[PDB]
Image 1 (cartoon, rainbow over the protein chains, first blue to last red):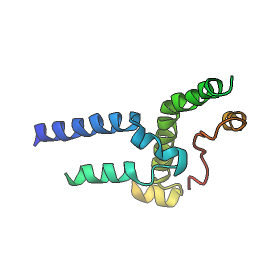
Image 2: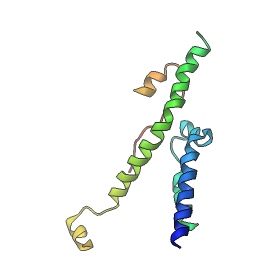
Image 3: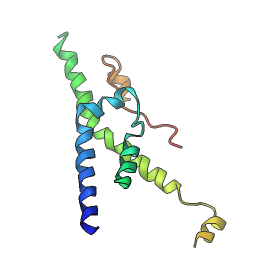
Length: 49
Length: 48
Length: 21
């Protein structure tokens, strides 16, 4: 339990940190205007995992 | 003068976004997070 | 101001902050 928490948490930061740099998530904010729940869902999903 | 020159300014905008990406996020979290706590003395004291 | 100046040549604009609620 102690180590599993250390694993899942580290993975998500590795993903969200690299997800913003790529143009996929970058182009969203030039047109949509905001996240649209991407960060909210990501954080929400992390709890479920 | 016509093609390359404007692109240089265009690169700056796409090259400057990676910093504004996080400032609004961090401010929007703490600002919204702090608003969750009560403000009234009666309600706040009841929490204690 | 940044978007206002860059608006003169390109449509690549950043995000505003409003109605945070």
